[PDB]
Image (cartoon, rainbow, N blue to C red; front, side):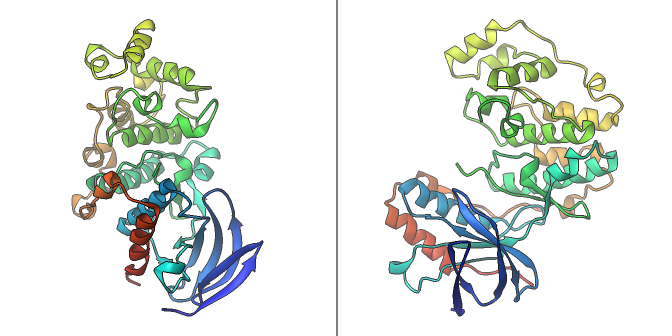
Length: 343
C-alpha cells in the first residue's frame, strides 16, 4: 500500500498516493471531479478522476463496476487505458471512493475539424486509427455506442485515442448527429455496426468540414439520413420490430440512394467508396471495422500484423442480479487486484 496524502482543493477532498503531485482542478460534474497531476512514477501528466458517489444505487454501483472492468480490459494504442485505480480505504468496510487515473488528454478531434476541412492524407490516418481501435473493441464484443469527435483524443502528431465509451439527445444537438438511425429511433436490437455508422459520419465531416446529418430533432435527422442513403426497402422493413415505426417509414415518399460523388465533391474516389460502405441503412450490410482496414483507402497504413485483437472479455455480469454491496465488493476486488501496465 502506498502512502496517501490528503487535501482539499476547490472544496473537494483528494486523498491520493504520494506519487501523484501538483494536483490542479480541471473539472467537476455529475459523474466526477478531475484534477490534472504529475505522476512521479511514470513521468506522465495524468488525469485523476474521483468518482462522485459511485455506490449510491444499484444502477450506479453496477455502472462503476462496468466502467472499471472495461477500462481494466482495454490495452491498445488507439483506445483509452487505465494507468491506475486506487482507494484510500484500508478495508472493504470503509470503501467508498474510487479514483481512476489515465493519460491527460489535450485536444479532441473537434478542435482539429472545427477549424477546417482536412487534407486527404490526414483523413486517411485519422480514420485508420479509429478503425484500428474499433477492430480491437469489437473483437471483444464491446459496442462503443457514442463515437463522435469529442470522444476522440488527438495529439500534435495526429495520434488518436477512442474515449468515453457509452456505458449506459433532444433537438439541435451534436451528440445525436453521429448515431445510427436504428439506435436513434429504437427500431431494433442493434449491432456493433452502429459504431461504423458513426465513423462514416465523422469521416464525412473531416472531408467536408461540415456535419453530415445536423438534424434539428430526431425526425428532421432521419429525413436528412434517408435523403442521402435512400428509404428502406422491404428487406429492411421486415427487421424493424415496431409496427408503428414501420407505418411511419411507409408514410414517407420513397427516395433513391444519392450519388455520393456528387455529395462529397472532389474527394478521393476511394474515400467516396468507403463512405458508401459505412453509410448503409441496413446495419447487416455495413462494412465491419476489420474489413474497412483492408480497404484501398488505407493502403498507406494497413498492416494486418499490426492491428491486434483483444483478449476475450467476460461480460456475464451484465445479466447478474446483485445487491449494492455485492457490486461494491466486486468493484473493490477489481481495484485491489489492479496490475499496472509496463513503463
